[PDB]
Amino acid sequence: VNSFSGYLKLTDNVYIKNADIVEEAKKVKPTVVVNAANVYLKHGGGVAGALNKATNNAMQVESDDYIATNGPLKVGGSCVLSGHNLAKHCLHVVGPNVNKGEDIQLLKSAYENFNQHEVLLAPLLSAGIFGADPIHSLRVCVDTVRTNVYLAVFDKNLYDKLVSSFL
Ligand SMILES: OC[C@H](CC(F)(F)F)Nc1ncnc2[nH]ccc12
Ligand SMILES: [Cl-]
Image 1 (cartoon, protein in one colour):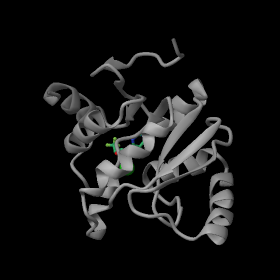
Image 2: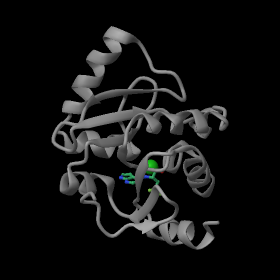
Image 3: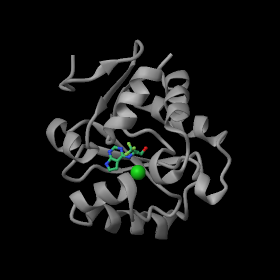
Image 4: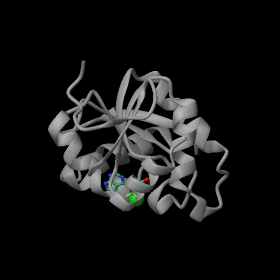
């Protein structure tokens, strides 16, 4: 039993909800919140910009030190950093960004990072400003993640569309 509330159960382990991931994280304070990151950990817009703003830019400060030490992530890769005031940890995961010409096949690799954590709050990888089809992202999530994932989807039309089309 966990403290996630109001989710629709799609499969044994995947749940979904229309919610702002920022407001969700502040309420649940999950062990892990997933950020929709880029390889430079520059949290300028989308989920990343929103999560960073909620940390008063502390996420960006920590991220800049991470990059200065380690260099950029790989597309499909991840790193674990602090969750600041939002969660214990933030798993920064880089899905492919279609608006940059990146290979959508890397979306499965991106979701594989979730399997290293027993429970996660997350957005749909490569959705939104990363320019991929969110129905496809949800399908890859369900077919790749085996741990318990609670998906927040900020857009109700999409949320309703995601539910009604789910196979
Ligand atoms: O796939 C990314 C997803 C796209 C869409 F909005 F349509 F759901 N974006 C988000 N999902 C959940 N919380 C969020 N907070 C800020 C942005 C954001
Ligand atoms: Cl977005």
